[PDB]
Amino acid sequence: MQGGGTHSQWNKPSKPKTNMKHMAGAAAAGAVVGGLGVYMLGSAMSRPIIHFGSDYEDRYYRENMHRYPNQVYYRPMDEYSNQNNFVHDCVNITIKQHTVTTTTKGENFTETDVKMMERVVEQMCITQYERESQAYYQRGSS
Image (cartoon, rainbow, N blue to C red):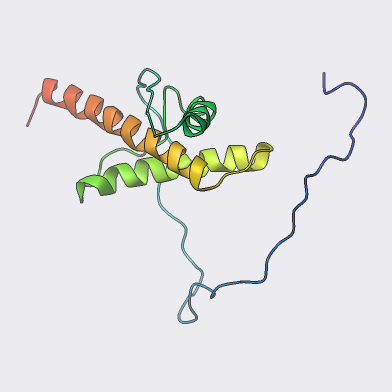
């Protein structure tokens, strides 16, 4: 049951730019690398409400939060480094996926969105890793 009628043509004004940075360098790149790990979920958390600083921002953080209301994508521990590094990986990734779902869908994404999608996920994940560790402390402990 696709939209009534057939396919049409809808596209908002868009024009590339003249910048082009460097090619990640130019040395021994025998086959670039990607990344070991994929998006996986476990437990979730209630939808939070971050008071950024204005209504606009709140409306954005809400319309996007709905994209990450309960779960966010992250990868098992099997690793330990800076404290903010863990969440960064978590959120920054869950973000790629979201910025990827909204950027492709039909919406824009500027400092406002990234700031919101990230703010929310960053903290949300904190709650996620907090729920994991907690279950750990209750587990056989160590």
